[PDB]
Amino acid sequence: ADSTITIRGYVRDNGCSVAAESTNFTVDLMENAAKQFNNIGATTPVVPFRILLSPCGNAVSAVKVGFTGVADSHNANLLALENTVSAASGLGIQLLNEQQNQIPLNAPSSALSWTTLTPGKPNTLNFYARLMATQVPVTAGHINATATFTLEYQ
Amino acid sequence: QELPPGTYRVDIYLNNGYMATRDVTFNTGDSEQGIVPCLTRAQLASMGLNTASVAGMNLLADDACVPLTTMVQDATAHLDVGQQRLNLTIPQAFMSNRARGYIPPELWDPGINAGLLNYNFSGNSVQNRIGGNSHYAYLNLQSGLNIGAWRLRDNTTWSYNSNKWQHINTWLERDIIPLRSRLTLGDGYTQGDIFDGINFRGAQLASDDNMLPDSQRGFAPVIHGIARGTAQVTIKQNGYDIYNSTVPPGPFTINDIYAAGNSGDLQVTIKEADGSTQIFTVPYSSVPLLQREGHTRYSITAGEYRSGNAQQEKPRFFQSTLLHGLPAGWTIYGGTQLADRYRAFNFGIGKNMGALGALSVDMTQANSTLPDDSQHDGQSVRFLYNKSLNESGTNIQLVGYRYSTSGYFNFADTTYSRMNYNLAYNKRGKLQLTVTQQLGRTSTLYLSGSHQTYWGTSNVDEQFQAGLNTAFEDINWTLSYSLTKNAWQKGRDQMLALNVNIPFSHWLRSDSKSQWRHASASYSMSHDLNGRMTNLAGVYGTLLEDNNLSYSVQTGYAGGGDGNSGSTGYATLNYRGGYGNANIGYSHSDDIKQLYYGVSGGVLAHANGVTLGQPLNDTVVLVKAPGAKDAKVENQTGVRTDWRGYAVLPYATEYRENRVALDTNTLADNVDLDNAVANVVPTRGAIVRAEFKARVGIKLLMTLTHNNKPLPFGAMVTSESSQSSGIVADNGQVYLSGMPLAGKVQVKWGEAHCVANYQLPPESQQQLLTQLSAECRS
Amino acid sequence: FACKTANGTAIPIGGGSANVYVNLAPVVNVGQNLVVDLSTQIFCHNDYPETITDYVTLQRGSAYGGVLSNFSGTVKYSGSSYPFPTTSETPRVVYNSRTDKPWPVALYLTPVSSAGGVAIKAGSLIAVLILRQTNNYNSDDFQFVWNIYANNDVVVPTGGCDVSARDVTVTLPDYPGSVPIPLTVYCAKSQNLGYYLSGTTADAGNSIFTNTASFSPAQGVGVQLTRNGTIIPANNTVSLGAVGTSAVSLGLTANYARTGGQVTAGNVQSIIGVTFVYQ
Amino acid sequence: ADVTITVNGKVVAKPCTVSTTNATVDLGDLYSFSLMSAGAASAWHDVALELTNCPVGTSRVTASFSGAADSTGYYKNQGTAQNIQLELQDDSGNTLNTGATKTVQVDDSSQSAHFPLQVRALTVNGGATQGTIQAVISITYTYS
Amino acid sequence: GVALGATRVIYPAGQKQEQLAVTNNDENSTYLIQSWVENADGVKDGRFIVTPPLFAMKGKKENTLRILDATNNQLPQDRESLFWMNVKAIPSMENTLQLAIISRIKLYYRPAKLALPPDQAAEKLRFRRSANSLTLINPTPYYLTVTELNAGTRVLENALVPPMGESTVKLPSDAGSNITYRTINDYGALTPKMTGVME
C-alpha cells in the first residue's frame, strides 16, 4: 500500500419533476346552443390532459394529489371561469380523475387519497375536463379559467 | 374527420409534435383520405427531417413538391380537420442529433482572454548518518496565455543540488470545431495507437475524442432495425434494462448505447403495436483499436523529432494515422510515416466477432536506414483479442502479441548518431496478457504480465503481476504478487505482500461528529522470497471542515536481503486551500532521515484583475462574484472565493457541462445572489467565466401601499440608489437584496407610477432581514 | 647432419628443408628486444662424427616473415651478434658429435616504438632463415630455408617498455561508484614515458567516452577515467616521469559520466585505448 | 593502440519518494434524479499522484491500481448507496479497473513525475438509491 | 418540469437559513416561482420567511431557496412543530386553462438538544386495538410518519402521528392478526419493518 485514493460521496433523495399541460377547449357552441340540460349538464367532449411526474426520485412512493381554485357560486364542485364581458355565462369547468369521477375541488388534505407512484421509473397521471352548465341558456363567449395543482408528498 | 380539399392554414405536427404553421396545399394522391400535402425541402429540413439521409433530395428545387410517400420508404402522412392538425410519421433514422447527451457547437464557450501561471516548488533535504547532508529544490513554472480561441503554453523549471533554468515544453493549441479536431503548434506528442509514441515540435491536426458525447465515445454495437408500424424498442443487458425509447414506423438506427464490454450481451426486442415481437441478440466485445460504425479518428502530424538526448539527431518526418468504423462490427485502419531516413505503412482491419470475441490484426512494413547507411527492410504484425464478461465471470480484457522481423526497426532507431540503444539486438516478439476473474460476490482475481524476445540473444524480458482482492463488508483484503525479470541483468525480482484496509467509517454512527470517521488503518507485510521481509502499519485520513488537510502516519520495520535492517516511520500532510496548496512530509528510516516540502498553486490574470487558487489543470472555470467573501463551491473540495469574490476551478471537463454551484449557507448575511447555480460548457484549454451577481447590503421586505391598498401582484420594483431590484408578491410584499440604509424606490406596473422612500434605523444592522412599511407618490 | 627438437617440431618437405614450430618468450631488453632464442629449442647431432664433419652457416637474405617482415634487428650466431636481416654470410659451426648440441641462434628486434606490441598467434610465420651446409670430405654444397612458426599466442614488444597486461576488462559497480584500473608499466632502461587516451568520445571536451555497449545500452551515460583526482581527456598526453625497473601503476580509475539529458537504465560499456609516447 | 581497456558499467533504476500517500476525493452531493437512468454518470473530479525525488537512472514509473469490484466490472461501493459504482480513468480516456497499470515518463529537470487521473461516479443498471459512497483504491508503484 | 431538492426539510433550532433546490428541466417553458410557509392549520402565520418569495425562471434554470426563521424562540421546544412548505410554480406566457403547480412538502421545526435520538423514535410506536379501529400512540417528541401499515395481510391507511399525542385509523375486523409497520425517516427512506406493540 504505497498510496491510497479514498472516495467519499453522498446521494441526496430527489423529489419529482412536475410538468403541467395547458388545456385548450374547442367545442365551438355545439352543446351551448342545444343544451340546456338542467344544472347537471355535464355533457361535453372531455379533453384528456395529463400531469407529468417525470423524472422522479427513488423515495417518491406515495403522494396526495388535489386541486384548488376559484369555485362557482352555483355549484361548489365547479371551477368558475373568468368573470369578464367577453366570457360566457352559466358555465363551470368540471375536473375528473382517470376513472371519470368528480374530483372534490378545494378539498382539505384530510379528504384526499394516497395515489401510489412507481419509485424510479417515470409516472403519469391522466385526468379529464369537461364543461358543466349552472345557468341556462349558455351565451357564447370566451372560456378562460385558472386553477392550482397541489402535490403533497408523503 | 374530412372536409373539402384546399389550402389549409393549419399547425403542422411531426409524430404528434407541433412545429410551425403555414399554408399547406393538398393534392390528390395515394393515401387514406385520397389527398397529400405539398411541402418543400427548406420546410422539411426545418421540421425535423435530415435531408442528408435521403439520397436524391438535394437534386429537387428549392420549392418543389417532394414526393415523400414514394421517394422515402415506409412513410405516411395524414390530415385531420376535426382538431385542425397534420399528423406525420417519419422514421427516426432520418433524424439528426439522436445522441443522448448531445451538446450543440454554439453552446461551446471559447473562454476569456487571460494570462496563466502554475507554480509547484518542491524539494527535500536528506540527512545521512555517515556522509553528510543533501539539499534539493525543484521549482515548476507552467506559463501560459489564452487569446479567444488560441491557447499558448510554456513549461520550464529550476533546479538546485548539493543550478540554472531548464526548458521543457512550449506549444500553441487550438480546437477546430468545423473539423472536429485540434491543431497543435510547437512541442507535442503523438498517439501510440498504430505507431509508437513520438515526441516532436511541429504541427498536428488530430481528432479529439473528448468532443463526442460520452454516450458515443468508444466502440459499441450500432443496432440497426426496421419496424413495420409504430413499435417500442427496449434493450436489456445482464438482466437489467439499459436502453428504452419509442420509435416511429419504418427503419431506425441506435448509435447511442454506453460502452460496456464487460456487461455481457445485448437483448433487443421490438414489440409492435399489435403484439408481434422481433427477438434477436447481438453479442458484445471490444478491442481498443476498434472504431464505432461511422466514427473516423485521424491524426496528421508534421515536424522535427525532439527526444532530449545528446546522442540523438533531429530529423524531419510525417505521420498520418487514420481509423474508420464499418458496419457489422468491422473497423479499418492504418496510417503512414514518411521521413528522411525512414518510411512505414500500416494496414488495420478489425472485426467484432462478438460470440467469438473482438479481434484486430494490423501489419506495419518498415524501410529503415541505420546511421551506418545500411538499409534494412521488415514488417511487424500485432494481434489484439478481447472477450466480454462470461457467465462464469471470465473477463478476458486483452490478449496481445506483436511479432517483428529481424530487419524491422522503429523510427526512433534511425535517429541516433553512432551504431554500437542498439540496432543489432532489436525486439522480436512481445506477448501481453491481462485477464480478470470475478470470484463470486466479494472477491476479484487480477492477472497481468508481458514477455519480450530479442533477435540474437536468447535473453527474455519478463514482467508478471497477480492480485486477489477480497471485500469483507467494510474491510478490503488486498493480496498481490509481482514478478519483474529483465534480460540485461541477473536474478528474478519478485515481491510478495498483502494489504489490509480497515476504515473507521463503518465502525461508528453514520452521523457521528467525530473526525475518526474520516480515517482508515492500513497494515501490510512484504517478503521478496529471498531473505528480506518488511511490515508496515499506518493510519491516514482527512481533517478540517471541507476535508482539505490530508494526514498519514505509518511506522514499521525492514530487515534481511543483504544484511541491512532498521525501523521505519513516515508522516505526510497535504493541504488544498482556496489560495493554493501545500505539502510537507517527513521520513524516518533510522539510517536515512529526510524531510519533504512543497507548495503549489494556480494564478489567473483575467480582465477584472488577479485571482489566486489551486494549481490549474488544462481547463479551468473562473468564478466571478464581486461581493461574496468566504463562498464555498459545491462539488469542489477546498475551493473558496477570495476577498474580492473571485475564484478558480482547477477541475473542469471539456466539451461537457460543468455545474458551478455556490453554497449559500456560507454566504455573508449581507450578501445575496440572483442565481447561485450556473452551467458552463468549456472547450479543451478554455477559461470560462462563471458569473454570479451579488448584492451587498441589507436584505429587507417592504410593504408598499397605495391609496390604503397594497400594490398589485407582479409590480416591478427598481432601486434608484443600488442596481438591485425585486418583484412584489401578495399583500404588497417585496423582497430586496443589497439595499442602502435609506434610498428612493421606483415602482412601475403599468403605462412609472409609485415612488417610495424610507430610512431604516442604524440599530437594525445586526439583523439578517428587517421588515418595514412605506407608501408612494402617485 | 640430423636435427631435432623437443616441443613441437615441423615436417620436412622437398628434401632437407622445412619450417619449425617453437615456443616464444619475448622479453624487453636494454637496447634491443629479444624475440626467439633458438639456442634452447633446436638440437642437432652428427650421425657420423668419426668419418665426416658437417659445417653449417647462415647465408645472407635471412630476414623476418609474415607480420614481422617489416622489422629489423640483430642475430646472435655462435655468441656473436650480426645485423638482421643479414647482408652477408656468417661464420660456420662445426658439427662432429653424436651428442645433440644446440644451434646457437637468437633473433632480436630493433625498438622503434615506446611501448607498443604486436600479437603473434599460434601458427603464423615469424622469420625466413637461409642455411648452408658443407663438409670436409668433399666439396658438396647446398642451400635450404628454415622458416619459423609459433605454437602459442604471444605478443612481442616493440619499444623499450612493456606492460603487465594489454587487454584488461574492469567492471564498474551498480552506479554511480567507481573501480581502480590495474595497469603497471616497467622499463629495462630509464625512459621519459607519456601516455595518451584515444577512442570514441561524446562531449566537446573529449573527456567522456561514449557508451559503446552491446545489448540494450543505457542513454545519457558515459565512461570517464581519472588518476589521483583529475580528469583524463582524450588525445591528451599524461606524463609519468622516469620509469625504472620497478613497475609503476598509472593510478587510473574508471567512473560514470553523464553525456546528455534523460538517463535510461541499462548496462554500460566503453572500450578505451592508450598509446605510449617518449618525451 | 598499445593497450585497450574495456570498462563495463551498469545503471539500475532506484525507487523514488511518494509525496501523495493518501489523496482524498469528495464527490459532494449527488441526486437520484441524475443517476436514475441506466448508464448515467456523475461529473469528473481530477486527481493526481505526485512522485518526487526520483534517483538518477529512473526514467519510467509504473503504477498498479487495485481494489474490490462488483458484477459491473468497476469498483464496488462499500457505502450504503446501492445500484451505483465508481470508475477510474486517466487523462487520455482509458478505464483503470481493479488491476490495470499505467506508466508515465519522469521529468528529468525536477526529478519527479505524476499521474494525471480522473474520477467519477456511475451506474450501469440505473436507479441509484440514497446512501453514502465509500471507496478505497490500493496502488503500488513499480519503478524502472 | 419543476422539481424540489428533497421531499422534506428539517429546521434545527438556532440555524439561520436552510437550502432547497428548485430545478426546472424545461429549456423553453418559463415559470414564475412563488413560495411561503403554512402552520399546522395550513395558514401562513409568518413563522418562516421564504427568500426569494417570488422570482422568474427563464428556461432550464436553477436556484437556491433559503428559508429564514421568524419565531425568535416562541414555539414549543419540548417537541417538534408542524409546518408546511408550498412552492407555487406559474407558467408564464385562446380560451385556455392554465394550471398552477404547488409542490407541497413538510417542515419539521426540531428543537435544539432533544432527548431521544431520531432513529430511536420509530420503534417507540405503540398501539391500541379495539373494535373496527386502531389507535396509534406516539410519546416521542417526533412526528412519526407511518406508512405501509400491514395488519397481517391486510394493508391499512397511512398516518402521521403527532409528538406526545395520538391518531386513529380505519381497521376492518376482516383482516389479519399480527401488526407490522414502517416509518419515513428524515431523509425520505424507509425504516426496516417492525412489530406492532399494543397497550
Image: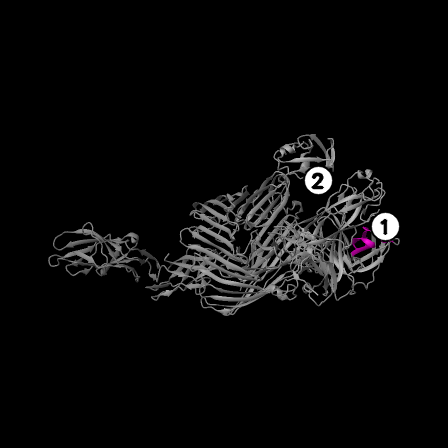
Q: Position of residue B419 (x, y in %)?
A: 43, 51
Numbered circles on residues, count: 2
Q: Which mark is residue B753?
A: 1
Figure quadrant of residue B665: bottom right
Q: Position of residue E154 (x, y in %)?
A: 68, 56
In the rendered image, residues at marks 2 and 1 fall on the same chain = yes
The amino acid type of the residue labelled 2 equals: Met
Residue closer to the observer: B12 or B762: B12
A100 to the left or right of B547: right
Which chain letter matches label 2? B
The amino acid type of the residue labelled 1 equals: His
Residue closer to the observer: B553 or B529: B529
Q: Which residue is mark 2?
A: B19
Residue closer to the observer: C108 or E2: E2
Q: Is residue E53 magenta?
A: no
Q: Position of residue B392 (x, y in %)?
A: 51, 53
**In the picture shown, does residue B4 fall above or below B270?**
above
In the rendered structure, which segment of residues is drawn in magenta? B709-736
B711 to the left or right of B164: right
Mark before the other along the chain sequence, 2 or 1: 2
Figure quadrant of residue E44: bottom right
**Which element type, helix, strand or loop, lies under badge 2?**
strand
Q: Residues within 10 Å of mark 1 (few under 14, many from 20)?
A: few
B76 to the left or right of C255: right
A49 to the left or right of B168: right
Q: Is residue C193 visible?
A: yes
Q: Is residue B727 magenta?
A: yes
